[PDB]
Amino acid sequence: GKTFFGQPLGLSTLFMTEMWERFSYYGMRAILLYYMWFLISTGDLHITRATAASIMAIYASMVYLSGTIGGFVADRIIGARPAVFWGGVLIMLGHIVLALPFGASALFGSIILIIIGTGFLKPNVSTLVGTLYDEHDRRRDAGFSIFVFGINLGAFIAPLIVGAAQEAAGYHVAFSLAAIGMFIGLLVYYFGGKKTLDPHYLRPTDPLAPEEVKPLLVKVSLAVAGFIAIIVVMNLVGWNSLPAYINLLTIVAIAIPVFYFAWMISTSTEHLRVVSYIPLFIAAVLFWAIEEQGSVVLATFAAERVDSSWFPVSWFQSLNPLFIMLYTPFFAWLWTAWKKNQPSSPTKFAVGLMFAGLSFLLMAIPGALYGTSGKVSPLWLVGSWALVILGEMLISPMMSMWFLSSSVGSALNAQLVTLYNAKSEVAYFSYFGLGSVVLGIVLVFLSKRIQGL
Ligand SMILES: CCCCCCC/C=C/CCCCCC(=O)OC[C@@H](O)CO
Ligand SMILES: CCCCCCC/C=C\CCCCCC(=O)OC[C@@H](O)CO
Ligand SMILES: CCCCCCC/C=C\CCCCCC(=O)OC[C@@H](O)CO
Ligand SMILES: CCCCCCC/C=C\CCCCCC(=O)OC[C@@H](O)CO
Ligand SMILES: CCCCCCC/C=C\CCCCCC(=O)OC[C@@H](O)CO
Ligand SMILES: CCCCCCC/C=C\CCCCCC(=O)OC[C@@H](O)CO
Ligand SMILES: CCCCCCC/C=C\CCCCCC(=O)OC[C@@H](O)CO
Ligand SMILES: CCCCCCC/C=C\CCCCCC(=O)OC[C@@H](O)CO
Ligand SMILES: CCCCCCC/C=C\CCCCCC(=O)OC[C@@H](O)CO
Ligand SMILES: CCCCCCC/C=C\CCCCCC(=O)OC[C@@H](O)CO
Ligand SMILES: CCCCCCC/C=C\CCCCCC(=O)OC[C@@H](O)CO
Ligand SMILES: CCCCCCC/C=C\CCCCCC(=O)OC[C@@H](O)CO
Ligand SMILES: CCCCCCC/C=C\CCCCCC(=O)OC[C@@H](O)CO
Ligand SMILES: CCCCCCC/C=C\CCCCCC(=O)OC[C@@H](O)CO
Ligand SMILES: CCCCCCC/C=C\CCCCCC(=O)OC[C@@H](O)CO
Ligand SMILES: CCCCCCC/C=C\CCCCCC(=O)OC[C@@H](O)CO
Ligand SMILES: CCCCCCC/C=C\CCCCCC(=O)OC[C@@H](O)CO
Ligand SMILES: CCCCCCC/C=C\CCCCCC(=O)OC[C@@H](O)CO
Ligand SMILES: CCCCCCC/C=C\CCCCCC(=O)OC[C@@H](O)CO
Image 1 (cartoon, rainbow, N blue to C red):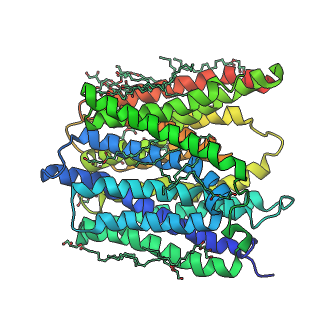
Image 2 (tube, rainbow, N blue to C red; image 1 turned 120 degrees about the vertical axis):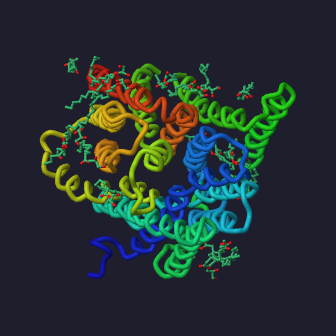
Image 3 (cartoon, protein in one colour; image 1 turned 45 degrees about the vertical axis):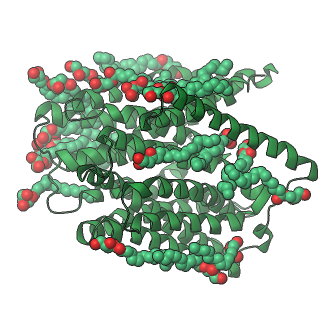
């Protein structure tokens, strides 16, 4: 019967809903760093380029950290379907803010809107995907992979369309197209959802019991009061610069897993098996750090060290989702072909880290051989994104912990990307790439012990 690639027809609605949100997100991130460079060059934004690179990282870290709670707010308060809609509305307004004839004053407002909007929409669209499949249904893994292709499809075409629009009609026009991209998703999601989506998800599936509202309000109130108390203390002692606030969000993002892990210990049944997660989680952190630097460090390398005089330099951001779109058909073949091998999930996380380390190690070669004073070939970045996406495919298959590793890895980037420049290029690439490889080699021994557990 009628399907969307063998799947329920509701997938096409959610497939396009997320493609257009990812089009709006990754089209914005493809030019946002260059937009901050431009505001710096005109004197409107009084920060260094190292700070702007750190802003891009802590931006992504907060976006994925905000996704760790959107599932809770939907499942318990507002509902999954209203969360996606109003989440996209906030995402749309965030891109409209950057389209207004403002400058650096509109950066923080746009960032807050997209952080909150993505937190509402991003996890709940995937939740609504699994609601098309009953728990017995076996097309789940096939349906989510189709869903991933739509994530990367919009992520691939966004820098091409938005980047070219920036170099032709300017930034404000380019950011408006990102808002239009989200608006297109809202139209298809609203009217398309009303036809094929279960109305049971217009409301929370686990609404708060009467006795649960007060302790939750206390819990939220104490967290906001403490976070505000820290900001007050910082301004009293003089720690009030923008890098100081970035350091605060970095500590907060990293303190969440280490506190959620330190007291997860207290039952020897899985007391050691809880520990087995740690090497897999920390490996996921360092990989997402390497992977998310493509929009920061590799975006900086493309703009300064590559002869890209015949196309917009923001198009290099399409290499990350392009290789995924190419690897997916091969990788679908691979996992069902080598059924007898069955690579253990721990072992995969090193190969993903080794590949990520290889991608940076490769990028240390052009500067060591030709120097950093000139321009190199664009195929260095093509070969670099070819290796890191290779590792992403291996690590590709609660999502909040998944959101958390990306947030911690991106929070780690908020500190490291400030070390990158033309004079530190070779050492930065070589040492962070070498250290990531040797930390993939230590996994072999640690995987064996996790295999035993
Ligand atoms: C999506 C971005 C990927 C771009 C990959 C480009 C692969 C290019 C390979 C050849 C090296 C650059 C050649 C420069 C070039 O031919 O310029 C033409 C001439 O006008 C001199 O600038
Ligand atoms: C005006 C600025 C507001 C910006 C809002 C950004 C809020 C981002 C994150 C808040 C939620 C942090 C709590 C995350 C958490 O503990 O969940 C992790 C847990 O689910 C692991 O599975
Ligand atoms: C209008 C205010 C901004 C939009 C409201 C949503 C702000 C995000 C979070 C508010 C706190 C909700 C509680 C989150 C929470 O308890 O997460 C628990 C965690 O275990 C999730 O699994
Ligand atoms: C700047 C935009 C302001 C908001 C304009 C749109 C508000 C107009 C009507 C409210 C529609 C709320 C729909 C919420 C919802 O859950 O939609 C889910 C979708 O699947 C349709 O059921
Ligand atoms: C419980 C709260 C968890 C912490 C979440 C707070 C995250 C809020 C905002 C993060 C925005 C990152 C910094 C944005 C920024 O620096 O841009 C403004 C700057 O351009 C103005 O000069
Ligand atoms: C459909 C509702 C949400 C979609 C966004 C709607 C608004 C999008 C575009 C309207 C025009 C954008 C403004 C373009 C602009 O002002 O920049 C050009 C000019 O300022 C620089 O020379
Ligand atoms: C300055 C540019 C305009 C700024 C405001 C743009 C807001 C325009 C339209 C609101 C979009 C609402 C979401 C789109 C949608 O599908 O809504 C359908 C629903 O509201 C119909 O009941
Ligand atoms: C940072 C500002 C956040 C503003 C919104 C955060 C709200 C967080 C916790 C309070 C949630 C109370 C919702 C009560 C509710 O809707 O359920 C009531 C009913 O189901 C109980 O019988
Ligand atoms: C629940 C216990 C609360 C005790 C305080 C918790 C937070 C402790 C320190 C937060 C420091 C914020 C980031 C450090 C900082 O501001 O560095 C400033 C430096 O970069 C120059 O301004
Ligand atoms: C008893 C709890 C376990 C033991 C405490 C573990 C430490 C807990 C939180 C610290 C978070 C890591 C520090 C954040 C970080 O590495 O960046 C520091 C930097 O941003 C300051 O400028
Ligand atoms: C198969 C893809 C992986 C290829 C990467 C393997 C190459 C490993 C390391 C190459 C970087 C060497 C760094 C050379 C170096 O730093 O020398 C110092 C001086 O020459 C440059 O400042
Ligand atoms: C899983 C498959 C991985 C296969 C990767 C094989 C790549 C082997 C070597 C690549 C090292 C980088 C190439 C260095 C190089 O050719 O520099 C010279 C270049 O300028 C030629 O003009
Ligand atoms: C199988 C992968 C191909 C081989 C990868 C190993 C490449 C190792 C180093 C990168 C090329 C070395 C660049 C020359 C160099 O670093 O020395 C320069 C320095 O001596 C000048 O003072
Ligand atoms: C699985 C893929 C592994 C990637 C293998 C590593 C290859 C990476 C870069 C090769 C650099 C070749 C650059 C030489 C070239 O063709 O362009 C010449 C240059 O002078 C034009 O600008
Ligand atoms: C069947 C899949 C095998 C893929 C693994 C091989 C990786 C793909 C390309 C590696 C290219 C090696 C670098 C080529 C090179 O050294 O530059 C050649 C250049 O000097 C010719 O002008
Ligand atoms: C199990 C949780 C995993 C935690 C992974 C994060 C590792 C903990 C702390 C990393 C701190 C990185 C500090 C970077 C640094 O100090 O150098 C950069 C600095 O100069 C920026 O101004
Ligand atoms: C020699 C250390 C054990 C080798 C383990 C295998 C690691 C994978 C590839 C070798 C990477 C060599 C990196 C060379 C390097 O880091 O040079 C640093 C350079 O800045 C100082 O000249
Ligand atoms: C075990 C968890 C590891 C997670 C954190 C790994 C990195 C931690 C700290 C790195 C900051 C120290 C910077 C060392 C350094 O000199 O690198 C900069 C150099 O490459 C350019 O000058
Ligand atoms: C400068 C030398 C560069 C090349 C060295 C890289 C390869 C050398 C050693 C890698 C494997 C070390 C032994 C790992 C091992 O088999 O331990 C047992 C482990 O498999 C148990 O799970």
